[PDB]
Amino acid sequence: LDADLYGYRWARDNVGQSGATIYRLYGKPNAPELFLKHGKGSVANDVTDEMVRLNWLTAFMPLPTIKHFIRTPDDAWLLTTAIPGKTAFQVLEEYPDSGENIVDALAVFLRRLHSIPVCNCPFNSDRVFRLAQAQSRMNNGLVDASDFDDERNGWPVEQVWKEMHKLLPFSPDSVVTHGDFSLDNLIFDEGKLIGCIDVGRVGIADRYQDLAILWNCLGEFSPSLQKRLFQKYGIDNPDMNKLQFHLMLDEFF
Ligand SMILES: NC[C@H]1O[C@H](O[C@H]2[C@H](O)[C@@H](O[C@H]3O[C@H](CO)[C@@H](O)[C@H](N)[C@H]3O)[C@H](N)C[C@@H]2N)[C@H](O)[C@@H](O)[C@@H]1O
Ligand SMILES: O=C1c2ccccc2-c2n[nH]c3cccc1c23
Image (cartoon, rainbow, N blue to C red; front, top):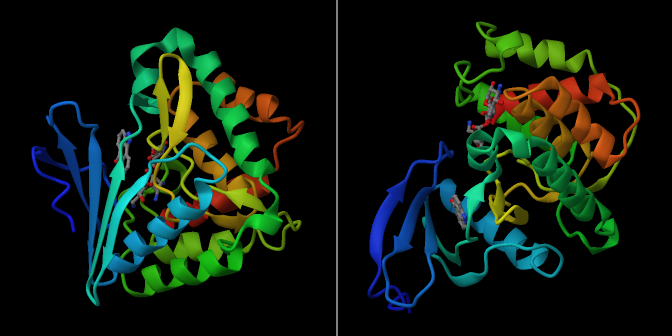
């Protein structure tokens, strides 16, 4: 029973997400901050997808703990503990001189996730799977041509779709990925990167799935920081074709 919510103050958080209602639970005497995600209709499946991934990935990485999860035919409710601290973005903005330490911490953390042996992963998040989702979102008109990257702004959804297809085929690579390795999804506390959130897309895919999203986020701070991500991670010459493909695929989500 969800009655383990008494004494909490409620707030509704718009973190620019897709679908799910996120409630922040705070102000309870000597009780931790909690988050409650609610998905209605098809969004119940997205909240269900996150719950399994949190449940599985917690044996390997630092993530929010599942306190309670409820599923009924149209609704999914996900109650978790919060990861204390600030997003990597908020940290980067407040302390520009910590850029290099943050990027290094992000690359080390991403290497840890990518190092989890694939033989442990029950989720498929590969290009073929994601291209199908991208296609259903384009054909349902759910893709927002407003939130596109600068090099693609003003482009109709179908231009991105056709141009992205010219970058294929590409070399086979498979590691355990986050799916949305952005500056808003990595949590910092007292200089250290303490965990990640928004694990709904976790599964086996190409490492550029995570590398491309973070690299792009770093583009709004410095090209030297974007360069250091690949240098700390350990890639000599970043695959720009793979980088562009993953950046274009993220436009449909
Ligand atoms: N639609 C919902 C999704 O919205 C964001 O993802 C979007 C990015 O924001 C866009 O990129 C822009 O914002 C980045 C900072 O995040 C900037 O670095 C970049 N220069 C900008 O062009 C990108 N083109 C599309 C991508 N789907 C959230 O991260 C994600 O959780 C959420 O699911
Ligand atoms: O949305 C969440 C969130 C959602 C579910 C679980 C934990 C978190 C979480 N932990 N720390 C932060 C900082 C900003 C946003 C969020 C967090």
